[PDB]
Length: 78
Length: 134
Length: 180
Image 1: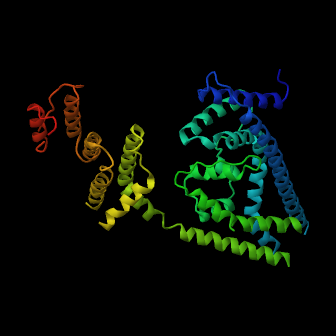
Image 2 (image 1 turned 60 degrees about the vertical axis):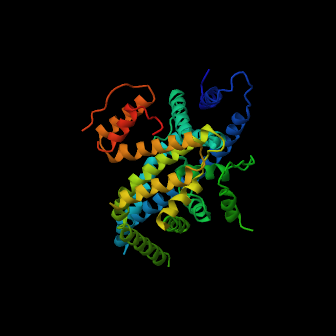
């Protein structure tokens, strides 16, 4: 039962693997979990990279906004 | 001079305000966009554009089903292709087709798997040779 | 412009500097003005694309036909390079209509020889269909379609003739000269 984003995301990944191997018409022939594993590792590394990039960009934008606010306060004081 | 600098940087301040407003939406949809892009890299190499759009329909249905929101105007080239790399590929010999750009991104963003190329025109040999040089 | 925006962000985050910021802003404004000045060539390109779109669509239809030929037998396949060389030799060997007609003639003369007599005849009939169904009118298209139908014994019915060229074809059908 789902209480976090992780169980949901695992459900998207398994459902997509099932739909993919269903429409490939593999039939009785076995389905390799290689696509599933590769997608999981790619998702892990890409979530880490995107979160780091978004944090860095948000920190830079916040620093610029703070500098602009300080300059505006100095201009209003003077 | 301070007033002139403020008037010049008002556009940058508005752009920063727009970025700060869109930061919440980006943080909300980051997990869904990462899911769709990783599924791109690990599934969509060996498919044509019709099958790619089909599994966009199924994948977006699954993201909307399990309450994970994504970008409505999402694109693989925009998400995982920089302008520097796009110009580098186009000047090294890659075609201007969006399908070829997506395939090139799949090829060049695969560091854990050895990429297999199906190029009946034998053009990607020259493209990757010009990309990597000597 | 993107690199200059990144450099400006890194310069403001790291902090004379006002002169460098003014120089970067002037460079960005000059780049934007150059882009706006160079963005005036769009209508000519749009007009050229709208002029040559019919030839492009007809060539795509011809290439799809030849790919469907190549799916039937392993010797009949076609690549984009040979088709593009055949397109290139057209200019070497109603301007839009003339270019399209020479395209049809040269593609048939180049790629008909790689087929047997039955597939040559199928190719000629289908190319005639693609040319005439676009150039001529709906009554012409339905007359050719019902002539092919009565040839294939799939649809029976006389076309509503007004053309002058189809008199010979109708004589061939009524006189049972199927090869002719």
